[PDB]
């Protein structure tokens, strides 16, 4: 018996991810599995493209393929919409705009299925350039740190999230990926509507040396933090 969703995250929780995608007509499926530990703000996952070769670079799918595993410090736990929506879960929707290129539109349901936290996703990508950084596979295999800004959506009883990912290109340039995100509870019960805050993300991408399928091994660390009001020197 659990009073609050956050109670479901005191220990290690198994994770499953299932993604079906279609980018410029190229269809694929990805399966992932691993575990999360919110007390540590950690998730470890391995992803397989089960349909064959992934038609886009793994790093472009990284944000798409679990904010409920963030470590919210004690003084911020009342701002944790993600765990509060559990076990029923939440819908996470994004549009991602790659600058001077296509966009991804995604919808995901993140909820418990038995003892397992499951992220099921549909992705549609359109208008990508055949010789651009995405379909041309010009991204480095990494994903730098980033702070994700969160704001309550009172009317939808959820949250809205915007951030810009800077993907490194092998020639030393950057490919911008503008993320617009919203999350709404699946269930009808009350959720915690957060004050404005951040999630700080780190991601580390690797390969299983024994794995011959197209795949990504992913480690994320994510911790919640407050905001500070920037001031220019003049006003200090």
Image (tube, rainbow, N blue to C red):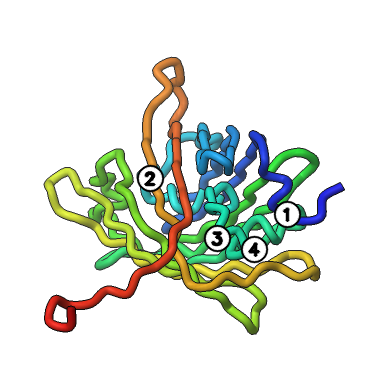
> Closer to the observer: label 1 or label 2?
1
Mark 1 is surrounded, within 10 Å at the Cα level, by few (under 14), some (14 to 19) or many (20 or more) other residues, namely some
For marks 2 and 3, give the CA distance.
20 Å
> Closer to the observer: label 4 or label 2?
2
The spot of residue 173 in percent (x, y) is 14, 53
Position of residue 66 in the picture relative to residue 145 (left or right): right
Mark 4 is surrounded, within 10 Å at the Cα level, by few (under 14), some (14 to 19) or many (20 or more) other residues, namely some
Pointers 2 and 3 in contact (C-beta within 8 Å)? no
The spot of residue 224 in percent (x, y) is 48, 56
N-terminal-most mark, 2 or 3: 3
Tell me what residue is drawn at x 38 percent, y 65 percent.
163
Would you identify the image quadrant in which residue 229 lies? bottom left
N-terminal-most mark, 4 or 2: 4
The spot of residue 209 in percent (x, y) is 39, 18
N-terminal-most mark, 3 or 1: 1
Question: What mark, if any, has residue 202 been given in the picture?
Answer: 2
For marks 4 and 2, give the CA distance.
23 Å
For marks 1 and 2, give the CA distance.
24 Å
Residue annotated with mark 3: 76
Pointers 3 and 1 in contact (C-beta within 8 Å)? no
Mark 3 is surrounded, within 10 Å at the Cα level, by few (under 14), some (14 to 19) or many (20 or more) other residues, namely some
Would you identify the image quadrant in which residue 153 lies? bottom right
N-terminal-most mark, 1 or 4: 1
Most distant residue in the front direction: 236
SS under mark 4: strand
Residue annotated with mark 4: 91
Residue annotated with mark 1: 5
Tell me what residue is drawn at x 26 percent, y 46 percent.
139
């Amino acid at each position: 018996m659990v009073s609050k969703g956050e109670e479901l995250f005191t220990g290690v929780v198994p994770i499953l991810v299932e993604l079906d995608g279609d980018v410029n007509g190229h269809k694929f499926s990805v399966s992932g599995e691993g575990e999360g530990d919110a007390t540590y703000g950690k998730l470890t996952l391995k992803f397989i493209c089960t349909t064959g070769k992934l038609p886009v670079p793994w790093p472009t799918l990284l944000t798409t393929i679990l904010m409920c595993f963030a470590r919210y410090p004690d003084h911020m736990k009342q701002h944790d919409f993600f765990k509060s929506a559990m076990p029923e879960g939440y819908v996470q929707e994004r549009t991602i705009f790659f600058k001077d290129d296509g966009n991804y539109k995604t919808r995901a349901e993140v909820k418990f299925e038995g003892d397992t936290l499951v992220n099921r996703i549909e992705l549609k990508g359109i208008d990508f350039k055949e010789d651009g950084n995405i379909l041309g596979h010009k991204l480095e295999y990494n994903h730098d740190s980033h702070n994700v800004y969160i704001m309550a959506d009172k009317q939808k009883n959820g949250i809205k999230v915007n951030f810009k990912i800077r993907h490194n290109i092998e020639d030393g340039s950057v490919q911008l990926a503008d993320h617009y995100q919203q999350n709404t509870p699946i269930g009808d019960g009350p959720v915690l509507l957060p004050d404005n805050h951040y999630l700080s993300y780190q991601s580390a991408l690797s390969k299983d040396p024994n794995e011959k399928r197209d795949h990504m091994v992913l480690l994320e660390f994510v911790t919640a933090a407050g905001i500070t009001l920037g001031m220019d020197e003049l006003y200090k």
